[PDB]
Length: 330
Image (cartoon, rainbow, N blue to C red; front, side, top):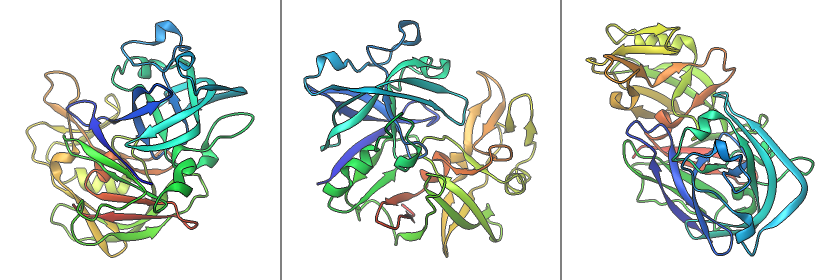
């Protein structure tokens, strides 16, 4: 089997991407944030505290003839941005882009933090990291991909995120029309539960490539590119007037600037992030100070190849017995 679904930016900055997901019988379609940095599929629901729901589409398990309470199971998750959610668990039929999993754990939110409430466009998350990170207790649950894997034509999924445009998540096949040149594959460590890999270096604009190992995660659920402070300083030093602002919470730059590209290495291959992808616009409406899309990972504890990086590439998440990651230009 295979599946193919379009993923759409939630706003004009590509702050996140939503992908429609069918849950239950008859189908209830929710727009979920596919997140290769976590491993829970959770949704706003009829059980979510009413004051914490503000415009989201909810899953109502009582209206699904295939929903079953997973008795005794609870979940609770905290994300890197400080947001969180928790609740109980149902199993139900879940379909993405024509690919169907029966008996998928659907984690129903009883509580969500303010950031989730305030984002009316995201109805929940669909985790695509390794199932070892799933938070369901006392019986850990499998991700949608893990459940689908054995039925897939090939045990892979691909992320093809657009810049200010829709893109695609495919399951079970590689669309050879969706990228240019060849795909370069690179090793993955699953030791922390992430799609963790080591970039071979970077360049800023037309500058020379610096060969240096940068361990980090491929994370579709993180907006920006978070890299070591040395690398980030080298980038922003090429933008007149750019500076790190503790009050804003990272690097800002004059909105009048033209940003240089940023290149990262994948083995001997190179992925070029155009400068425009690094512009996240005014820090507040009407400001001439703009927020940068490359930020320091110092104090995160891990480097994160978020959407800014991934949307510059066609990315293969290979879930074979020994997982790997592939990157192609597009």
